[PDB]
Image (cartoon, rainbow, N blue to C red; front, side, top):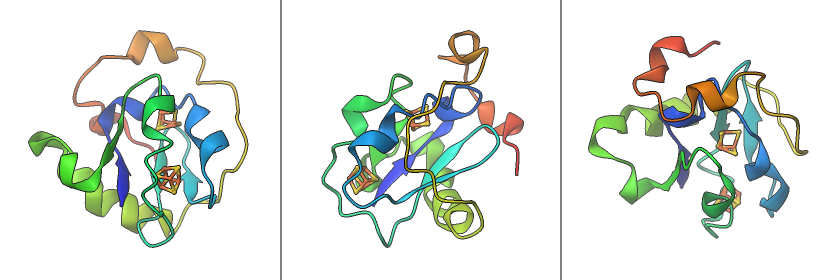
Length: 106
Ligand code: SF4
Ligand code: F3S
């Protein structure tokens, strides 16, 4: 019930996965999502994200409410990621840029 939002796109640091007790993170080309049914809400991944893109479902910003359903539907099609990887090459350039959902890759 924790949701990855907008600032993850084009950053994808992947520090979030090393602290997940249940391995419920699924990866896309430039984005990660959380499988809402497997997540146990221990909140351990939220302070680990450099993009600060992870939020508890009831705390997801009003203008990013879309990502709640997005994480559930993409967690169903993307592959499981359980290990840390290097961030995307220009992650710091995109950290803090808004409306990055227009750059989301399936
Ligand atoms: S809140 Fe806990 S169980 Fe849910 S995705 Fe984050 S680390 Fe994994
Ligand atoms: S940028 Fe994305 S890959 Fe994890 S560390 Fe943050 S939710």
